[PDB]
């Protein structure tokens, strides 16, 4: 599943909803610390839509438990990421993924 370790609290009231556009900064790492993706390098927020299957399952599941202004470390098991196949490029089979995520806005 998804483990959430809070670095900075959100308001604890305002969470992502169906029909909303989620606006976040994120950085994705393997367990060994290596980066595979980021929004922070381009220095601009990344947007994705709840329920629209635009990101891996674990990432959305984690974000949906975050409130406005929260920054957290999401630990995501392979079965809700890329699983036994991994993905072309950095991500190997059975990769538990680490995401540094900040929930900036909901549009």
Image (cartoon, grey):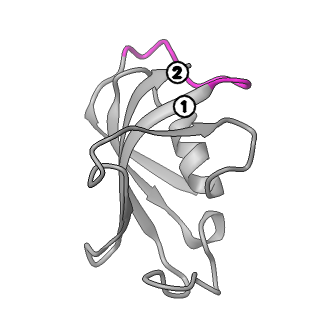
Q: Is residue 59 left or right of residue 40?
A: right
Please name the predominant secondary structure of the magenta segment in the image: loop
Task: Give the mark nearest the N terminus, 1 or 2.
Answer: 1
Q: Residue 51, percent across and down?
A: 74, 39
Q: CA distance from mark 1 to mark 2?
A: 5 Å
Q: Is residue 52 above or below residue 85?
A: above
On residue 106, the disc is 2
Q: Is residue 66 above or below residue 96?
A: above
Quadrant showing the N terminus: bottom right
- Say which residue appears at 48% left-offset and 85% top-offset: 89
Q: Is residue 77 left or right of residue 28?
A: right
- Crowding around mark 1 (Cα neighbors within 10 Å: few <14, some 14 to 19, many 20+) is many
Which of the pair 67/87 is nearer the observer?
87
Which of the pair 41/28 is nearer the observer?
41
Does the magenta-highlighted stretch encompass residue 105? no
Q: Residue 15, percent across and down?
A: 54, 21
Specify start and end residues of the magenta stretch as a single range: 11-20
Q: Judging from the image, what secondary structure is the residue with disc 2 in?
A: strand
- Say which residue appears at 26% left-offset and 55% top-offset: 41
In the rendered image, which quarter is residue 85 located in? bottom right
- Crowding around mark 2 (Cα neighbors within 10 Å: few <14, some 14 to 19, many 20+) is some
Residue matched to label 1: 22
The answer to whether marks 1 and 2 mark residues whose Cβ atoms lie closer than 8 Å is yes
Which of the pair 32/104 is nearer the observer?
104
Badge count: 2
Q: Is residue 28 above or below residue 12?
A: below
- Say which residue appears at 42% left-offset and 20% top-offset: 68
Q: Residue 38, percent across and down?
A: 36, 57
Q: Judging from the image, what secondary structure is the residue with disc 1 in?
A: strand
- Say which residue appears at 73% left-offset and 25% top-offset: 18
In the rendered image, which quarter is residue 75 located in? bottom left
């Amino acid at each position: 599943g998804v483990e959430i370790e809070t670095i900075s609290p959100g308001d604890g009231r305002t969470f992502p909803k169906k029909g909303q556009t989620v606006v976040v900064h994120y950085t994705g790492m393997l367990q060994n610390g290596k980066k595979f993706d980021s929004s922070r390098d381009r220095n601009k927020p990344f947007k994705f839509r709840i329920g629209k299957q635009e990101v891996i399952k674990g990432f959305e599941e984690g974000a949906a438990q975050m409130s406005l202004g929260q920054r957290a470390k999401l630990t995501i098991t392979p079965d809700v990421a890329y699983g036994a196949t991994g993905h072309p490029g950095v991500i190997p089979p059975n990769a538990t993924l680490i995401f540094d995520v900040e929930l900036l806005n909901l549009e």
